[PDB]
Length: 341
DNA sequence: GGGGGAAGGATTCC
DNA sequence: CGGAATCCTTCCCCC
Ligand SMILES: [Ca+2]
Ligand SMILES: [Ca+2]
Ligand SMILES: [Ca+2]
Image (cartoon, rainbow, N blue to C red; front, side, top):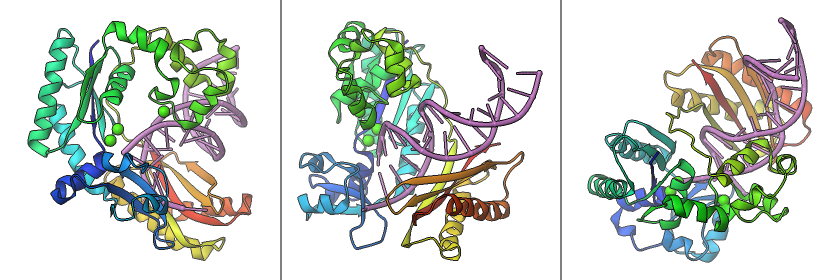
């Protein structure tokens, strides 16, 4: 198996650089403004000229504006990035049919039946990089290895605008001397949680006992890291479909008033059904972010599709169930639909 | 004992 | 002091 991984570099910010070439060379920060005070929100994407000064995705906008006060701060236009991303994805499927779109800015290509060795794959990645650059002016990073995890690791090491092949020998080497926190799927919570057991490298998960690792980081991520340490990970490249569509809005003013929250919730439903397009959902969940930024959610699955009018009635019932079983105020309210037909 | 699925909190990531 | 989506553990019914 030879998997090729393509990751669009700082995608959100690069599309803004492409749509306005006056921005390249300058620090660019793509933000999400909730709309409470003037600069309330978070950073979604920052280019590398902004990441060098500590501006990274996740931090508040005012924390970014304290570091780079005159950097270019633009609002996030997800609909634009999704259309550009879909165009690039269509270029990728001309190189292989077995494609796994993992996110808006990355996809896995199974080029086992198109390429003999890692040299042919490296030359294929160079042509994929040039094509994306020629047709969309977007630079990507290419990772090639024996499975999806190490193909993504290759791109993680050579980003941005890079290419890297991890052969069978470097895999066994990376198993011993790669930080466990830089394994795909290992976020911050599991990483710090893994440091509390001395687990710093991938090889160390074998020298521990399974039930100890299972009770701490969960059985799922336990078997995941074990299979990688045994060099037995070989998950296939499968077509990924979108399973959930929802929209959450930050309400102006916190509230526990049903009539005050309903307009936001009904607005969230309308925008959710518009993005649903022809998809008919059978499950609906009402989710609320409390004043202390905690999340509470109530759901309900139907034996049939949910019409928009049914979603209106059921969402009020679920939101009432939230207010009945939690006494905190609500800061953000929203809905999510799943279990399509 | 566990299949099968629903509920919803917990993580990951742009 | 965002927001989208998936992950994944528990719980439940019942054969
Ligand atoms: Ca990216
Ligand atoms: Ca990515
Ligand atoms: Ca990580």
